[PDB]
Amino acid sequence: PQITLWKRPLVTIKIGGQLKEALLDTGADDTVLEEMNLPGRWKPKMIGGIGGFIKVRQYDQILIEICGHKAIGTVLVGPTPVNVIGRNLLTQIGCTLNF
Amino acid sequence: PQITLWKRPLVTIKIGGQLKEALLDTGADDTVLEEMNLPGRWKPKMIGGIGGFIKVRQYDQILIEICGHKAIGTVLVGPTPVNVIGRNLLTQIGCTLNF
Ligand SMILES: CCOP(=O)(COc1ccc(C[C@H](NC(=O)O[C@H]2CO[C@H]3OCC[C@H]32)[C@H](O)CN(CC(C)C)S(=O)(=O)c2ccc3ncsc3c2)cc1)OCC
């Protein structure tokens, strides 16, 4: 679909079997979700944002459905202000910017 | 144009008579640029993301040219680690997400 930007581009995602709401974020290299329980191994990682760095749990090769489009990739879980879908998954569902 | 997301969506902007590089960032409500002496009055503001908040100066009705497309709106100036073009200006140049 074509998504305009007058409102936040929030979409429904399915991850770990649970539905969540997330922001399509072209300024994010990586996908970062708020604290949740996810099945699978994870490793400690750090990521930097506008205000500095935070600690996250890095889950690899996670299945995630974004508006019905399937992606399988890295998901970071930690104290982000909002769930963000980053370019690592936006590229998998074929997302481009157009103007 | 059409911008894929394999790499950071960086573009050249013209603001305050100067050329800069900035991200087209659908996850940013507002436009945030590196420290630069814009003339005119401004208001203090705090904006938050991953890692916490930074202090910025809010300038209103600022002209920016983005890859040949002109836009006018609020620009926040401060010690941001990267320049982001946010939705307040992306809507003006007719930018959409497409997948
Ligand atoms: C020099 C490198 O420094 P650096 O490595 C990190 O630099 C950066 C810093 C910020 C960005 C853009 C942001 N991306 C992001 O956080 O992505 C992270 C996840 O993926 C990784 O890739 C990029 C970083 C990692 C988002 O697109 C937009 N944010 C909001 C969302 C909801 C979080 S916003 O910026 O907080 C923002 C903007 C306008 C606004 N108006 C009212 S609120 C408000 C908040 C890109 C690179 O370390 C720090 C020293």
Image: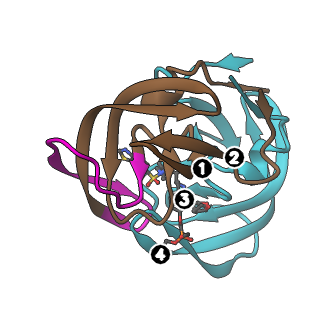
Chain colours: A cyan, B brown
Using the image, name the chain to which the residue with label 3 belongs: A
**Labels 2 and 3 share a subunit:** no
Secondary structure, mark 1, is loop
User: Camera-side residue: B51 or B76?
Assistant: B76
Q: Nearer the viewer, mark 2 or mark 3?
A: 2
Mark 4 sits on what residue? A53
Q: Residue furthest front?
A: B17
Q: CA distance from mark 3 to mark 1?
A: 23 Å
Q: CA distance from mark 2 to mark 1?
A: 8 Å
Q: CA distance from mark 4 to mark 2?
A: 22 Å
Q: CA distance from mark 2 to mark 3?
A: 29 Å
**Residue found at x 59% / y 18%:** B94
**Residue found at x 24% / y 44%:** B58
**Labels 3 and 1 share a subunit:** yes
Secondary structure, mark 2, is loop
Mark 1 sits on what residue? A27
Which amino acid, mark 2?
Pro
Which amino acid, mark 1?
Gly
Ligand 1 closer than 8 Å to label 1 CB: yes
Q: CA distance from mark 4 to mark 3?
A: 19 Å
User: Camera-side residue: A60 or B37?
Assistant: B37
Mark 3 sits on what residue? A36
Which amino acid, mark 4?
Phe
Quadrant containing the C terminus of chain A in the rendered view: top right
Mark 2 sits on what residue? B9
Asked whether residue A66 is drawn in magenta, I would say no
Within the image, what quadrant is residue A91 found in? top right
Secondary structure, mark 4, is strand
